Length: 55
Length: 48
Image 1: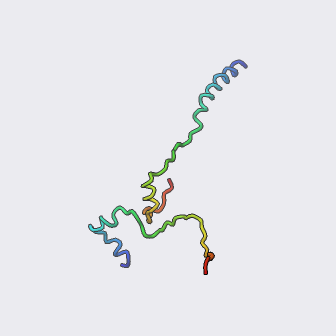
Image 2: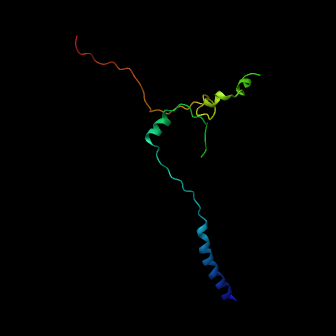
């Protein structure tokens, strides 16, 4: 009787250790500097055309 | 009638002016600038 639940937990905890890898799901995006000429062009321009963007 | 009567009158010539807008006139973006202050200071004159 006791050995049954002991083996049940024995396999179940290995199953849990396998399961746990799925939890963390972060997004990866990198940052890079503008080209110098393009940066100067963007800084110089006076009107923005489209108003705003959130991404 | 009113300004809208002109606004809607899109024509062939506009392919060069308002098709695919790159700027607007109605929202200025101001650029932040280096912090500074300015003052008038008298310098010493050497000589008569």
